[PDB]
Length: 503
Ligand SMILES: *C(=O)[C@@H](NC(=O)Cc1ccccc1)[C@@H]1N[C@@H](C(=O)O)C(C)(C)S1
Figure: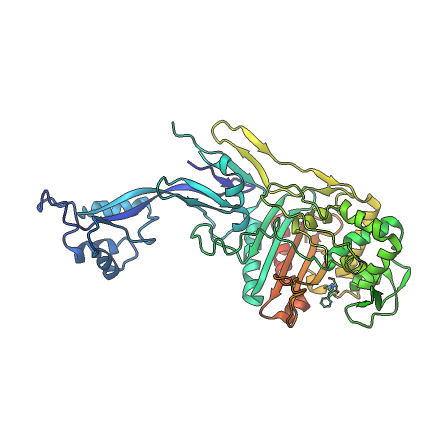
């Protein structure tokens, strides 16, 4: 009996269950008595009396009850997975030929729910043996797999209440923007526990609908050009190095890099503005400037020290390292605002954690334990671990003040992320998406990966929410303008209420 998969609070995300399959013996070959038949005689009337319990298709049933030289028949999917009452109901009616075989099915109480984390187990029909095909099911299969030995349970950090907030919000963003890719992740700011994680498009582990359309888990196995969320790590390196003074002025506008003209987003700039306002506006010239002040060799190192270009070493299979793009000054200067370099969303959460743990990066984790439920032996137990301390408490407190302004500055271009009654901070991102098949960047009206790396309450946050949407195929203009504010706001507002945060 395959092990359970539980959430933070012992609520069930996957379990084995006893269901029943319907079998009808149609062929008259059980004729040792016409008075005591063991096959289906009146087809019309046998068909009608189980319509009362099954899908109620008396014609489709009577149709299927008519085949060629087959003793037994099944009724595909609507005649598998039937309750223990559905058995006793059909057994009371004493129909001849009709029996119900027991079947052990894998059952996901919440259906489409953390589907790409939890994964799916598939049944060998010959043995009823279940094998994990993706996610926790696949990773921890040997632990979950079971004279009759009962398999070990896997406990996640996922909180079913928060996971719901995330599932509703991403459901809305698909109706509004129908994007090619989309994800949101809630993490405990102070522990690095994944409290909630979802992505679209995804599958239903229960029904199996859409399974194997996308193998890739967004949090761990998919890489992105992060965009301007990645500026927080460059700003931290610059604050530590001395390059960044919020009140010093810099020449905004553009820079000429290996002959190409990389410019601020409004193209003109704002002339000489303070570096604080530079960041608040998301000036690429500020970041290319700070890179010149600090040094190309010193900045590759600073990115490496924030955990980039190498795997977080988490519990997920085939975790992507990504890569720091640093082969020519065009790659380095574009890396400063999160193009060329590829990240995993989990790398970004590891990095971002440093601003709230006095400079200590938290290794993010979702598996809480693997225990036998009889013996109570923990074969594995996860905990808060430090992944690096790339910056000082001071650097961190100052990166925080900039993230506060990005949202709450009177000249903010990101007030769409404010939440009535809770103070929020973070950094926005709009980024070009590499074309799957070489061909530089995806073309179109606004062919962007919009993203936000927020946290609340500000300075001493309970949670970090990192949502990202890639290539909205509808309201693509509103996508560019609002990014992921329509997912961030509800996810964050409901998660703070549920953790009883004041206001
Ligand atoms: C960071 O990713 C920056 N993005 C770019 O410079 C690329 C870009 C994409 C669309 C339009 C113009 C430029 C800055 N990040 C976003 C943001 O802060 O939301 C901006 C569009 C302001 S530029």
